[PDB]
Each structure stands twice: as structure tokens, then as C-alpha cells.
Image (cartoon, rainbow, N blue to C red; front, side, top):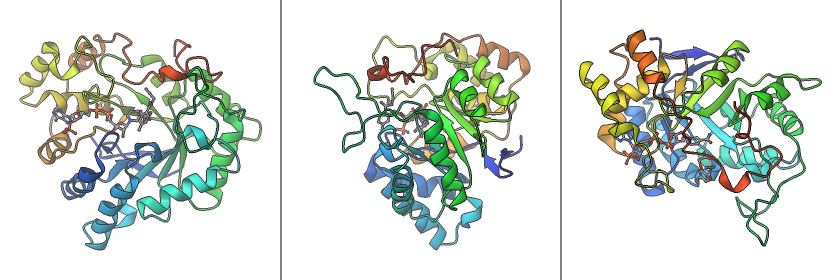
Amino acid sequence: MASRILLNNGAKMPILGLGTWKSPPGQVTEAVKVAIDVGYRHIDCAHVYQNENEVGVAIQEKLREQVVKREELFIVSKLWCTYHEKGLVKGACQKTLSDLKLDYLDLYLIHWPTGFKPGKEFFPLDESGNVVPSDTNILDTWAAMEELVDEGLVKAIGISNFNHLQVEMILNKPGLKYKPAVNQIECHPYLTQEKLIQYCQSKGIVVTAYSPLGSPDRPWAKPEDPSLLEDPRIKAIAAKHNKTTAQVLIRFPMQRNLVVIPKSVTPERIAENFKVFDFELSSQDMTTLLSYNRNWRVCALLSCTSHKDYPFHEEF
Ligand SMILES: NC(=O)c1ccc[n+]([C@@H]2O[C@H](COP(=O)([O-])OP(=O)(O)OC[C@H]3O[C@@H](n4cnc5c(N)ncnc54)[C@H](OP(=O)(O)O)[C@@H]3O)[C@@H](O)[C@H]2O)c1
Ligand SMILES: C#CCNC(=O)c1ccc(F)cc1OCC(=O)O
């Protein structure tokens, strides 16, 4: 298992990164510092997570300390839905750069295919509670992303939560200048994504798996929901390999040629989660884990199910 995967922009991306959604601002600086100390070279960020300033403090301190060089880091962020407008994309990217203390991003993603009305609110609602859309389409937003590459602000651009028809729309864009490098999607044994993964990989687009542990800290969790970390079938595979259940859940996408971004703010778990380059799941193990699919989503974007670009009506 090599540590990096080659992207279609010619750059290499570390296959294991640190997630930062829900990482409290008072804990995430330490989390990222510890992560870099124990070997992480890829951090997954987003403006909407409201903690990029604090992530940036950690990155900058480790650069200043010469623990790592900037070229050895792979920093990812995402354009939020209220910034899909041509005239807002650069400023959104620049705000993220300023917060992260960087002069470029390694990868910048369209966070969701759905554009929302610009303004202070991340989810602008009408008087009845539906998200208020933007009229700006996926293709014009993509053109704005391409401009960021040409201005030196980002080294690669990609997409997140795009279904295969939406990926296809970009690939078929008239005058397409840069193909998406990455599609970041939810993926774990309860949402195995075989169809979408195959499609993206066949087009040379690298897939990043989010919520690989099933996001037990997701704010809308309910007691009756399935739980990957507590699934005795997965625990059994972990026990056989003398690893933790989380380590199995992280190794699983790695062996499918995916990038994976487990989140933790717990120093011991941050270190644990990185120790996944010392064992191999068998083909049988992999197929067994795949068999647990139930099309269950942590992130279903439920306030946007009527948006013209809602991604999850399509089968994949
Ligand atoms: N593009 C998108 O739309 C999108 C959507 C969702 C997520 N993401 C990205 O993907 C990252 C990962 O997804 P996620 O945050 O939803 O959830 P996740 O990585 O599947 O799970 C995070 C949870 O697992 C716990 N955990 C971590 N390591 C553990 C271990 N070794 N043993 C037991 N529990 C462990 C964490 O606890 P502690 O932190 O307390 O240790 C936290 O509660 C996000 O942080 C974000 O960067 C992107
Ligand atoms: C379900 C769903 C869609 N996402 C959200 O509602 C959301 C909102 C804010 C945030 F910080 C993370 C959020 O979810 C994770 C993400 O989108 O990266």
C-alpha cells in the first residue's frame, strides 16, 4: 500500500487524511498538530465547518517548526453552497486561504452540487422552511473553479456529493478546461457505492470516502440507527487481524483505491487511525465488508430534496 495516489492533474494525494467536520474550534488546533506529528499529510477542511482559522493555526505552527514542508502537505477545502455565483467563488476561496494561512490549496471542491441564495446564512430558508436555491448551474460554477487553477489559488479542483449524471454533466461541459480530480462522497460498509465508484474511477477521477466510521458524532444520530463501529461482524474481522474496528473501516476504502478521511479530535485515536499501513484485508474480507451495504446515508441533505440539483434521487 503506497501512501499517495496520482491525480489527473499530475499531483500525488495522500490516501489517508484527517477529517475536521464537528471538530470543536478549541480542540482542532491540537488535533491537527498531533496528526501532523504522527504522520498525517492530508487535512480535509471546509468553510462551512466554521473551524478553518483554528485548523490553519496548527498547519502554520507545524510549517514554522519545520516539522513538515508546505510541499509535503495536501490541504483540501470546499466551496459552500451559498457561493456558487461567478462573482463569489474567488472571494470564498480567498477567505478559506486566509483562514488556513495558505497561499494555495492542493484541492478545492464544490461541496454540494446544489447552489443556494447568497447571504450570511449557510442554509437560507423561505418562510416555509425549504432551502432557497440559486439559479447558477453546475457548469458555470465549474468554470469559476477552473479560473482558480489559472490564478494559482488552487492546484486541483473537484466535486463532492455529485451523482454520476452530475459528474457526466461536467465531463461533457462545452469547453471543459480541467476535469474534476476528485469526487468526495460518503462511503463505508453500509453505503458501498460500487456503481458511482466504478464510474468515477473509469474516468480517471479519484474518489475520497467520507464518514468512513459512520460518523457516530453526526448531530442527527438516533439510537436505532445502524452502527459500524459496534457491528459484531466487523468487530470479528478486526479481531482476526489484531486491529481495531476503526482500523478495519479505514483500511477497507484504501484497498478499493480510495482516499479516506476519518475524523478525530482524540490524540490516541488520531495516532491509532494512521496505523493502517501494516496489514491487509483479504479479498474475502473485502467482499464480506461490501456485503453489508444497505444504502444508508449519514449525509442526505434533507432540507434540499426539491432542489433541481439534489443528488440523491438518482440511484447513483
Ligand atoms: N464532503 C462532504 O459533504 C462531507 C460530509 C461528511 C464528512 N466529510 C468529511 O469526512 C470527515 C469524516 O467524516 P465524519 O466526520 O462524518 O465521521 P467519521 O470520520 O466516520 O467518524 C468520526 C467519529 O468517529 C470517532 N472516532 C474516530 N476515530 C475513532 C476510533 N479509532 N475509535 C472509535 N471512534 C472513533 C470520532 O470521535 P472523536 O473525534 O471524539 O475521537 C467521531 O465521533 C469529516 O470530518 C469531513 O472532513 C465530508
Ligand atoms: C446532511 C447534510 C448536508 N450537510 C450539512 O447539513 C452540514 C452543514 C454544516 C456542516 F458544518 C456540515 C454539514 O455536513 C457535512 C458536510 O456537508 O460536509
